[PDB]
Length: 241
Length: 241
Ligand SMILES: Cc1cn([C@H]2C[C@H](O)[C@@H](COP(=O)(O)OP(=O)(O)O[C@H]3O[C@H](C)[C@@H](O)[C@H](N)[C@H]3O)O2)c(=O)[nH]c1=O
Ligand SMILES: Cc1cn([C@H]2C[C@H](O)[C@@H](COP(=O)(O)OP(=O)(O)O[C@H]3O[C@H](C)[C@@H](O)[C@H](N)[C@H]3O)O2)c(=O)[nH]c1=O
Ligand SMILES: Nc1ncnc2c1ncn2[C@@H]1O[C@H](CSCC[C@H](N)C(=O)O)[C@@H](O)[C@H]1O
Ligand SMILES: Nc1ncnc2c1ncn2[C@@H]1O[C@H](CSCC[C@H](N)C(=O)O)[C@@H](O)[C@H]1O
Image 1 (cartoon, chains in turn red, purple):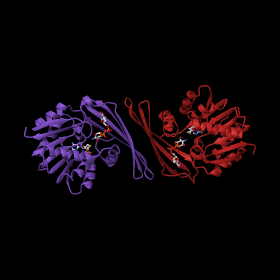
Image 2 (tube, helix red, strand yellow; image 1 turned 90 degrees about the horizontal axis):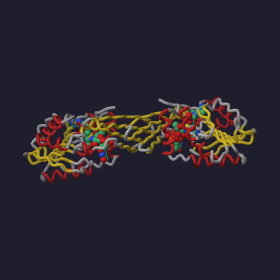
Image 3 (tube, protein in one colour; image 1 turned 180 degrees about the vertical axis):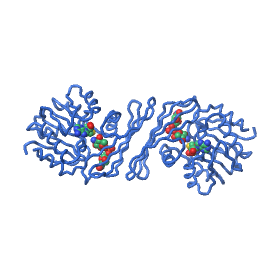
Image 4 (tube, chains in turn purple, orange; image 1 turned 60 degrees about the vertical axis):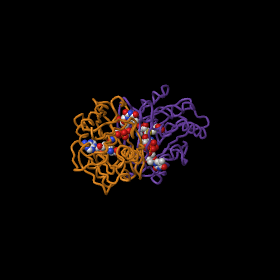
């Protein structure tokens, strides 16, 4: 079933990622510091595929003006409630045009893997370049590479919130040039009983040199740092190559 | 869903109840001690609704001859493999006839709740009495009574065993004079990927006087003891009444 971050799946996103130990406060701090390394004076940040706008809520404490772009209306609805004073655009990272430039353009937690093929990767990175200030920095957190992805990987966790128990379990396979991650949820609580939910995605296993080539074609210089927020590293790009 | 202890549900049974902390070793030892209290020289035991035969496997070390009865073929299959040298019958606790009598007749973990109302309860207790020796004892672990059931109860647990992860979540409500328990599972492993299973059962909340009535109509004296292996207590009955 779903591949579009919507309905109950969208409502469950923050809770399950908090449950899994994702620390958006620490990630934002680190992002902020990294942005300031490359661009001492940095003042504004666009978060592209900002999802439920968690990083944006914390980055607003480091940057004077933040903005987001998100494809999923249901994710976007959450992020707007969380960030009621920022402008958050409903739109596609492949094609957007905001009429303005930012000190940082960020794209976090491997949202970039929802792109297929070099053409789409090149297009996004070109849009990212089209929205970054001449002394700013673009930051893209890749998906795993084909060489380091671990097929067969199972994640399972349970979290409780407000009397509701939520169990999420994922299985990931190598399905050609993408990971297939299939994720099932069981939600249960005394009054609502039990419901079952599912999502399934192809997340593209772009090689390191594929991302590098996307940055380059977009006029950015590209550097890679191993590790990073989720283990997959981080690319940063500076205009002027 | 399913109400019939079959297929992968039967295959997951031992694993999920082990994960919940069910200790058939201790339960069997306590049961043997209780049988010996009422029938010091008890030597044989029929476990009715023996399921996958866990109690029977431990009760073998206490009684010279153990035997089982079980309605679900798939549960029975597993119990026979576990208890290769005992006779395990395929049939129905409401209407069975094995041609012999045992020092103890047991019916454990609220399998009695799978009967629909007083007439079926009466008939099973009369079959229990027909298969007990004159100086033996019938043991029935009841379902919850209506006064001690908690509607809205949620159980949720995840266990991993041999490459596989298994999450089981249950939710219970009051439906007439029974509990509706709905149980969802997620099973995931590296090679097999992820599947969702479900069962639903209607387990009758017979009152204490209902059970007592059934023992008495079967010719058995009855005593209830609170607590028990599962918190639901334990009835024992002795022929001769
Ligand atoms: C720990 C580890 C994981 N993996 C892969 C296995 C699997 O595809 C993924 C972790 O699965 P998960 O924890 O269920 O996924 P995660 O929370 O990272 O979320 C990922 O998938 C969801 C669907 C997207 O919305 C999200 N943006 C992705 O990060 O990373 C590896 O390749 N190597 C690893 O060491
Ligand atoms: C601990 C406790 C449990 N309950 C009821 C709530 C729910 O109906 C049940 C526990 O749910 P569970 O732990 O998922 O069920 P359990 O492992 O005991 O298994 C029960 O249901 C399954 C379907 C049967 O095969 C089994 N023979 C039954 O014991 O017992 C209560 O009413 N009060 C309680 O304090
Ligand atoms: N073409 C596209 N344009 C914009 N957003 C996209 C997209 N394809 C997928 N997405 C969004 O990518 C995000 C993946 S989840 C990551 C969410 C957020 N960046 C965080 O760190 O939590 C989802 O919100 C999804 O809706
Ligand atoms: N009418 C009937 N006759 C015999 N067994 C029955 C039955 N109705 C349900 N059952 C069985 O009762 C069992 C409930 S689960 C309990 C199994 C076992 N006594 C244990 O302690 O683990 C299941 O095996 C189910 O198949």
